[PDB]
Length: 99
Length: 99
View 1 (cartoon, each protein chain N blue to C red):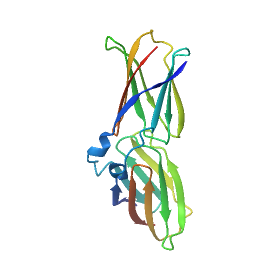
View 2: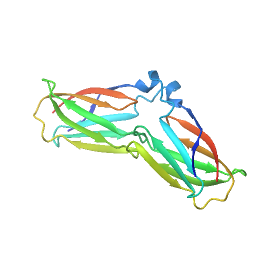
View 3: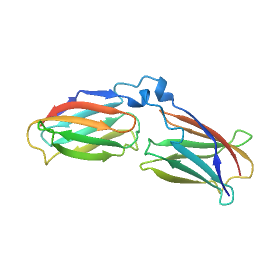
């Protein structure tokens, strides 16, 4: 029948310096796209974009199941200054950009 | 055009103890199933099972895109004693079980 397997977890990330370039984010202000390039796969991460009046104007969850480029579509946004906030249990990422 | 957005990452996980029950592993020796229950979503993780001669008898990548239970079928395996090893860039997990 069904039995618990006693496991031990070694969180190597807690003793391993992280690559400053694990994530590279770009904005294309012509096509109104955000491009997120992950060097390795990663846990799902929530992406929020906030305007100058603190309105959340875009929210999505990205599933980086493989290394490579993930695109987010910001076509519905006005021009202006935006804050990018990405988060999950492991990391919080902040940046700013203009459309 | 396309412009780099400077981002600052805060790796919360590097300074935060992780719930020892983040992952619960079970084995059903009748159905020859391994069951992996994640409390939260997680990065893709490689699952390897080794026999007493250290032959790798099962190897697969799991994609824990949502919290919940993931099942792996071990029908190819003999009755016997096995070592479990699961790993990605962030964690290594070890346990042992019987079929």
